[PDB]
Image 1 (cartoon, rainbow, N blue to C red):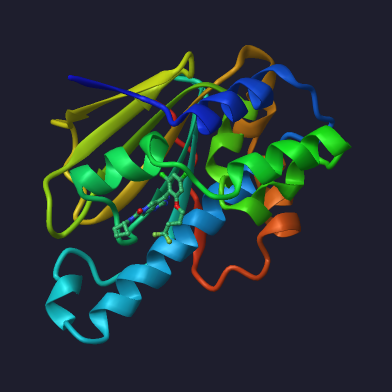
Image 2: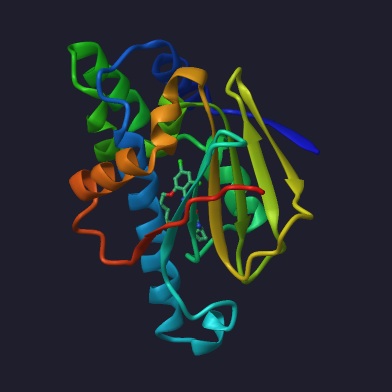
Length: 210
Ligand SMILES: Nc1nc2c(c(-c3c(Cl)cc(Cl)cc3OCCCC(F)(F)F)n1)CN(C(=O)NC1CCC1)C2
């Protein structure tokens, strides 16, 4: 288990998002889905010069899996995924050029759904999630898991669970008062609102253990 610190601006934003109120916290789903689509875009781009790269899965898509038992909403894509370095760099440690700008707009009163515009729309998941786990697998590396509950740091281990062919899985351990987003009905409407121009298939798998 490795522990890493967040780049100071990202760490600062996370604390702003967590502690500020918005009437409007569901744009986080738009964001993780946009991310997934870009990942899909990416592996698709790579495969145009090398078919073999799709030997870890020909289908390109996004699943949504609300789990009420475990109070977790999961977003899964068979996209490009991340190598270990990719994971450590892109989910906290390297400065994103839009972080400052976005914090100023928030200051000026900008609504939170602006966040997509600044390339930091992932950290919006912490509007609804006390904890986030990202499990990723890239053709060029083994499978890893990234964890953070904010508070300045994240961790990275290898993940032993169910091997993905390829892609990324963002698991949201929801806050107590954010459980409406496990509601099938709530997820139907949200996708229909913020994600009707996503060029990949999106399926809703409702998970319940017996
Ligand atoms: N679903 C999903 N997949 C991926 C990523 C994210 C993501 C996360 Cl978890 C957190 C944040 Cl802050 C942003 C994110 O994405 C922004 C769009 C990235 C783009 F998709 F364009 F690659 N989310 C990141 N990834 C890589 O960096 N891959 C390396 C490119 C070489 C392999 C795959």
